[PDB]
Amino acid sequence: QYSLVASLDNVRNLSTILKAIHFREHATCFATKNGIKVTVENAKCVQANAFIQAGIFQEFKVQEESVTFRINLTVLLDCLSIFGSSPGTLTALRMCYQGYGYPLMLFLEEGGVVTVCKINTQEPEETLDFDFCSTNVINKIILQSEGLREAFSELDMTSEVLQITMSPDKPYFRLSTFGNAGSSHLDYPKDSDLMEAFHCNQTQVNRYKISLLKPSTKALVLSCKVSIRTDNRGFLSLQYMIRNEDGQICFVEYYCCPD
Amino acid sequence: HHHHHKFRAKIVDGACLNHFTRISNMIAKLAKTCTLRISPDKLNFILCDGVSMWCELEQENFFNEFQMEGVSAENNEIYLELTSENLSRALKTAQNARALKIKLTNKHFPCLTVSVELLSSRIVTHDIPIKVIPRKLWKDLQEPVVPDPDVSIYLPVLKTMKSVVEKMKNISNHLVIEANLDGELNLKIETELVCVTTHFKDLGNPPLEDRNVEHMAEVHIDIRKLLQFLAGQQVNPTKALCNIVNNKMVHFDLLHEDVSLQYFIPALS
Amino acid sequence: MKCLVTGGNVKVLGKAVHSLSRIGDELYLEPLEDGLSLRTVNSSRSAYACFLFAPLFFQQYQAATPGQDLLRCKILMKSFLSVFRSLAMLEKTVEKCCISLNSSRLVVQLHCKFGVRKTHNLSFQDCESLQAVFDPASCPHMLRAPARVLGEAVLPFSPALAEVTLGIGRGRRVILRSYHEETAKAMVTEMCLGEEDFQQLQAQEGVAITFCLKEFRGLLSFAESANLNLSIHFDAPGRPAIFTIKDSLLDGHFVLATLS
Amino acid sequence: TDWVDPSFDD
């Protein structure tokens, strides 16, 4: 009967990753046999995708070969964390979506206490397609997230753009901002211990609206590794390898158009 | 600007000292202004806004020295209005202190003077401005008349309630709290976009034209006032009763260690 | 000018900038023969703060800018504070800090772990010297105590308390009392200290001065985290109070006006 | 919409 049935012994395996893309009020959800993909977009330039594969869930059954509904992400996250944001004391989740015109059902249980949520779903609007293929990627860098987490959290937000330079030559990998105070450059050498993979065949310099890229910090903090790619269009791809509380690996992705 | 009443007290027991601090901290959250009642055997903190609060301390259980007298022997009481934050700030020094002295003074103006002895000796003196309430108004500062509840039920873990309520606050400001005589209590918020219901069970009920045990008594309240009360409960009490008068009021009867706390939240509509 | 800072002194420099930022909105830089001078004043110029870093505080110190006159400049405090805003990261990540004059911008390079380099190109304004002489020895009254003692003394007050009164009472007691300018009354808080807490107390009894606590916290915070002694030199009410700290290779002194 | 295509050296 139910189009989508998902269950978790630990609700944080869903809520934690969703928080990393929470920079808009609403989000589009896609449920296939692979798992759940939640998409958040803004200004038709930036898009964040959270991927929670079926293997994460203790139970994940889907009927039709694609179930898509839009929802209030803020309300969803409020409900998923209804028993607190800092609990061996877990909170089980059972997620049920009947179909079009029906609300998303959430059954959360902690210590015998049961919270039942029913969130109405809106008309899904067309999800942007950034058409980002690996066969068109010019430069690619994989970094240890820990050594970049706090340096990124500090980039001057008074600046309008974040300029990313990737090059086979010095400074190899540079993040630049241009705010009121002046110029600021953050450089990572290709020989660095933070640099796990360096594949820059061509010098590329792209600029992106920093307001669009700022929420990706949330993903960076949760990630253990981060992959940075630009293509022949200048489009940016940020992929975050996230290890949840069960040691399982899920992914968050950020696309952003050039400025 | 004279007053023929007086009050002097002292705390030397560290447990009582920390305990006295937690209470002032709790009160500061519930209201900005509070009335302190001093009697030869008790201290009361009174709120009467529209939420009422009756907090009662038995003096012998905190003070090793305690002495007071009202204006008259017949009416041996003292009613003091003060800003809750002032007492809280003053008593934050008293936490893990060596000794605490409190005294009614009138240096520049009538004050509740809190002297705190810190150990290197260092003395911190807080002069808490107080408003002496005339005897005429004492009638408006008595114990609240407790109506017979339709349902009385033991509260769940207050820390669990707080977590649920504060997250529910992010969604709506109108909360329905309901309970029956079958150990069940629900917290319900409901908007056009989302309905949220939290189910507590096996809570138990205190004993004593009887009603169905499954019949649910409820009341619509301001969720911020419930959250106010729950946030002020840093520690889970030895006794936590939830009394509901259907569509009129919820009454919380708490007893933790020495301290009794009566909190009343009126129906919103 | 070129100033190269290494080791623990990097965080120390950062703490000084933090301390100065709680006084004024503009940071004045002036490399001298006896070291780098960082100064500021509050909006009404009723407060004056100065940190002097000895040449040997730096791994490399060149006051002169070859081809230029001697640097006398000011930068927006918030801008300079931004470079050192997280002290916890200064310690863990930053190994070296280089401050130099490129002739357009003031360059601050942070040489960090794993070969990471962060470069700040700050804009500045050529301006007047902020040097002003305030001799402590001219003050009749003084006291000295560990900064942590005074930190404890100020703890009971509200964080929003603007002004505090420092006074000398009977029994050579040192009194800190909250000050309030007068239709609802404010709670008066008085911290009372024994002279045992003080390393030196040279002040007639009955003498009291009222100054800005917010600004006093600024200097005190630096001296606390460095575990240094703090001297307070003062005179009559209405006359400025001079707050001094001394380390092996740096000097810090704050000058605060007092109420009349 | 397509599932994630990890670019990590896994």
Image: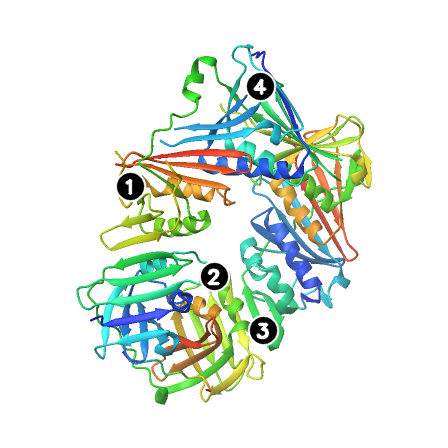
Label 1 is placed on what type of residue? Answer: Glu
Q: Which residue is mark 3?
A: C117
Chain of the residue where label 4 is placed in the rendered structure: B
Question: Which residue is denoted by mark 2 in the rendering?
Answer: A89
Please indicate, yes or no, whether residue A253 appears anywhere in the rendered image: no
Q: CA distance from mark 3 to mark 1?
A: 63 Å
Q: CA distance from mark 1 to mark 4?
A: 47 Å
Q: Is residue A65 above or below residue C230?
A: below
> Pointer 4: residues within 10 angstroms few (<14), some, or many (20+)?
some
- According to the picture, the residue beneath numbered tag 1 turns out to be B218
In the foreground, B141 or A139: B141
Determine which of the numbered discs, if any, sits on residue B109 in the image. 4
Residue A10 numbered mark, or none: none
Q: Please state the horizontal and vertical placement of residue B249, each as a whole percent of the image.
A: 32, 34
Residue B3, image x and y in percent?
57, 12
Whether label 2 touches label 4, CB < 8 Å: no
Residue A52 appears left or right of A151: left
In the rendered image, the vertical position of residue A183 relative to residue B249, given as above or below: below
Same chain for the residues under marks 3 and 1 in the image:
no
Residue at 41% across, 56% down: A83
The Cα–Cα distance between marks 2 and 4, rounded to whole angstroms, is 53 Å
**Chain letter of the residue carrying label 2:** A
